[PDB]
Image (cartoon, rainbow, N blue to C red; front, side, top):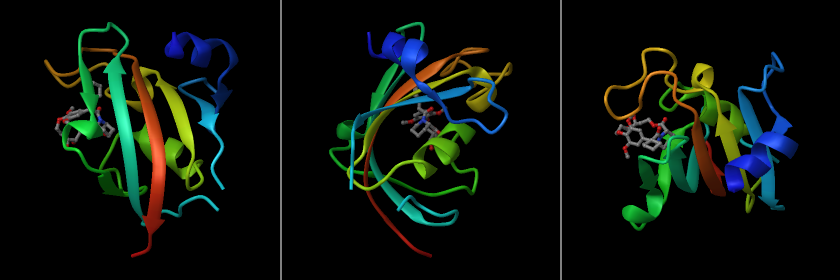
Length: 126
Ligand SMILES: COc1cc2cc(OC)c1OCC[C@@H](O)[C@@H](O)CCOC(=O)[C@@H]1CCCCN1C(=O)[C@H]2C1CCCCC1
């Protein structure tokens, strides 16, 4: 499974090196975005328990947020900042970099591990 591939070989991109955010490049792109930059991605995500999914392709469009401004979970602010234009990466994320012990009830259970596929389409400035 894609999660498994991440857990065994994936790159630890956390500062603390605690394996809370792991990354596999699936496609190499072609500069990575700065804090405050406007980011454009396609993503799919899911809970480790296999009980919930979500995809940008549902909106049939890109997901957009401002990098590093805590508008998304910490894993994204860290993860997307490591990506180049064109890149597709998988991220496997422990709760400490997502919704923690409190979770986001009932959407995200307590202590949930998450997985995302992210394609970095572009990124503009403030
Ligand atoms: C916890 O709430 C959601 C989580 C997710 C998707 C949602 O809606 C499509 C959610 O409810 C709407 C709130 C959104 O504005 C945003 O605040 C969520 C922040 O989400 C994130 O930071 C991350 C990264 C960006 C994509 C969304 N993602 C999520 O955690 C999804 C989860 C992913 C696991 C499957 C369930 C939804």
